[PDB]
Image (tube, rainbow over all chains, first blue to last red):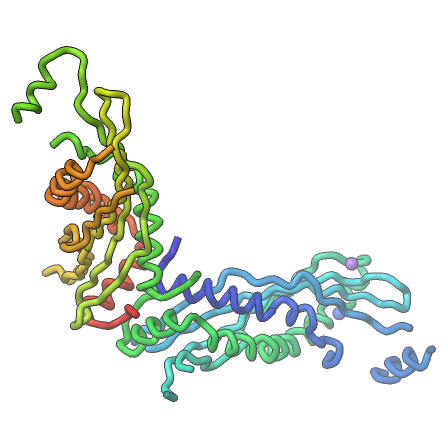
Length: 197
Length: 193
Ligand SMILES: [N+]
Ligand code: NA
């Protein structure tokens, strides 16, 4: 089952991310930190328990993708990510929405010189990767009256959040990859040779 | 466990050989099958001169080296066996031997006139100066006789039975491992440390 560089890099990346650890990073996202208006936020806190609450669970990593530029000098790894968002309200003590979330992080890997060598270029959220799906709901009301408003803000906040949280890690994983694996992959890029087919 | 090509190649070969399966081939070597005293034993009815068993077949760490131009590759396949010598005539054992032998497979990348690149074996040979022999009522006499014949027969026998295998293994290697190695050899690029 030993294989070539392409299959070795993605296998090595995954193992690096998981010992990062990515899943913990994907469980401890500060979604509320960022996500009338404040009057309610104030009335509930001063209420002396309420508001809505959001739990992050079932974080997961899926099979990485790998694509190489036609010229052969650049590598683009895509990192499919998954989380579930449990939307509740402690006030009534009920769960209103259960969402499944999927998102991709597209990291570009470059070869660079500074006397370590295989480095992260652009880390970003792939456009169109964010798929929010309804898993469960208290009833027809939150689904017909809350979801779309909720997902709407989510399509605006999450991607840049995940990118910012995940993106540092992959760089830490690139530097720390097997020395000999890196060396070989660099050679192939420098000479614009295809190893991802 | 994920490494570069060199590291990956060695592990791939080791797993490939063992599941080949190399050990069985070494045990089943036809050492015996190979004048007056010889024909005499045949004519009598109820007698067998001597027998040899091969035991404790073992595969050691492969060695890898790359040519200076970076176009050819030389993998070293260290081998080990134990030879127990018996005389079935009497019911006795005789002596035990430890034999260590090295096989050297050269691995090349050649370009086809049709732009296709194939990875090719040619050639495999028992490595000169590899064969080593050690001792585990008297028996000092035959020892030099057994040592002498082993010294002029074994290496070619092992080469003959083993390197057909390695050739089988190289064919069955991972498609992308081969394509990656081949590209780097045919473009003269070092990946062996
Ligand atoms: N809504
Ligand atoms: Na629910």
